[PDB]
Image: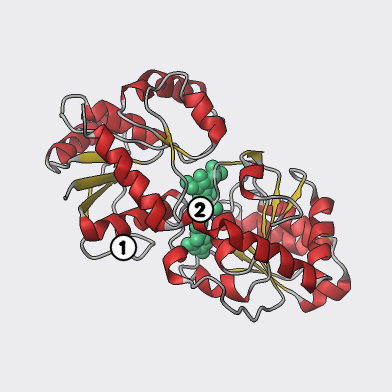
Amino acid sequence: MMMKISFIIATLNSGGAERVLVTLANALCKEHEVSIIKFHTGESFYKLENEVKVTSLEQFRFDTLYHKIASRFKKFFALRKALKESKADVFISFLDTTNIACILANIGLKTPLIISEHSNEAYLKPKTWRFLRRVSYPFCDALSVLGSSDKVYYERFVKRVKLLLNPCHFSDEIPFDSSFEKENLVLFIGRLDHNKNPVMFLKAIAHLDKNLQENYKFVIAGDGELRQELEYKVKSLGIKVDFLGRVENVKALYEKAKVLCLCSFVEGLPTVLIESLYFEVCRISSSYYNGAKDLIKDNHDGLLVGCDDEIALAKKLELVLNDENFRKELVNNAKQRCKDFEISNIKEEWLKLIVEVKNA
Ligand SMILES: CC(=O)N[C@@H]1[C@@H](O)[C@@H](O)[C@@H](CO)O[C@@H]1CP(=O)(O)OP(=O)(O)OC[C@@H]1O[C@@H](n2ccc(=O)[nH]c2=O)[C@H](O)[C@@H]1O
């Protein structure tokens, strides 16, 4: 048949949620009809299919104490307005702040709201939002949730929670079993904020053999608030890491690169650890909060280090990089996880969930 799907997100900037949304949208787009409603005006970082109808809420002023409070009622009713005027068969919204907003704004309309947590339940640190999520989330119609520990957490107070994986858009593009002629390149891809923890990457490149360190290229794709101080500490330790910062063509690095390191303290299902599956990139990652083992059979299809162990990382790095027959084995076992992220399969459960929610 057919449905109007409306996606509601804050921004469409170089993120992980926005990466999933567009993969789905681009895929549902062809059979169905897919509006996106995004708050912060601007363009999308990710090539968005042409049929995807995209509508941005207004720009609002947050100067003056008046406009500081007023622009929330104006935003809210501007949101309720767009939702009404989408006449969508279903609303799917993304991330806690946007999710709680949508639940309130949707109070009234007779259309289903899906909402999805896209990060471990413990990330939401403050006390008010952790509370508003507890009161408002049982009023949605379903709930997408990535890690199992989050389903066990959200099932306590939400009646319909589903575990949907993320869909890797590379799954259709990159043929399974492709020759990759790699280059001495280690990749760090991600936001340069405190949790993503890029400093541990630097500290660890410091501790590598001069042999390796002088023949390998190290690269930090991504930008954050740490992009300045990271460059300072790169001098303080004195290594050669090439900050590129928000590079829309990560496919180009993902090929040449041999290894990819993730250093974050807590995550849900990082797509950087999913995309590598498609490029014979070997993953090395901190045993981050909770969902670590769901993604990496340590020493079988990846390598896990203690959280924030600058040395542990370097050893594992030096381990793979002094050993091509190993790196090459790990990834051939990692190719095995590729299916668990094909958009084709992931899309149809989104479609399945939309159907049951559209009944009642
Ligand atoms: C701390 C945290 O809770 N992170 C969550 C994560 O656990 C997942 O749940 C994920 C999916 O919902 O969302 C967040 C990931 P987060 O926002 O941190 O991003 P991620 O690591 O999962 O992936 C983001 C990345 O952006 C891209 N990129 C990077 C650099 C660049 O120059 N250009 C790019 O396009 C990548 O291709 C990529 O997929």
Res 295 label: none
- Residue 66 appears in the picture as rendered: no
Q: Is residue 283 above or below residue 196?
A: below
As helix, strand or loop, the secondary structure at mark 2 comes to helix
Q: Viewed as shown, does residue 324 lie left or right of 103?
A: right
Vertical side of 334 occupied by 160: above or below: above
**Residue bearing the label numbered 2:** 340
Which residue sits at x=88%, y=68%?
209
Measured Cα–Cα span from mark 1 to mark 2:
23 Å
The residue located at (54%, 34%) in the rendering is 148
Residue 284: horizontal and vertical position, in percent?
A: 70, 56
Quadrant of the frame with the C terminus: top left
For label 2, the crowd category at 10 Å Cα-Cα, with few meaning under 14, some 14 to 19 and many 20 or more, is some
Which quadrant of the figure has residue 290? top right
Residue 240 found in image quarter: bottom right
Q: In the figure, is residue 264 to the left or right of 148? A: right
From the top left corner, tell me how far across and down residue 69 is, in percent. 30, 28
Crowding around mark 1 (Cα neighbors within 10 Å: few <14, some 14 to 19, many 20+) is some
Q: Position of residue 65 (x, y in %)?
A: 32, 30
Q: Nearer the viewer, mark 1 or mark 2?
A: 2
Point 79% across, 58% down: residue: 204
Q: Amino acid at mark 2?
A: Asp
Name the residue nearer the viewer: 281 or 172: 172
Q: SS for tag 1?
A: loop
Q: Earlier in the sequence, mark 1 or mark 2?
A: 1
Q: Are marks 1 and 2 in contact (CB under 8 Å)?
A: no
Protein image colouring: secondary structure
Disc 1 marks a residue whose amino acid type is Leu
* Up/down of 180 relative to 269, above or below: below
Question: Which residue is tagged 1?
Answer: 48
In this view, the residue in front, 118 or 215, is 118
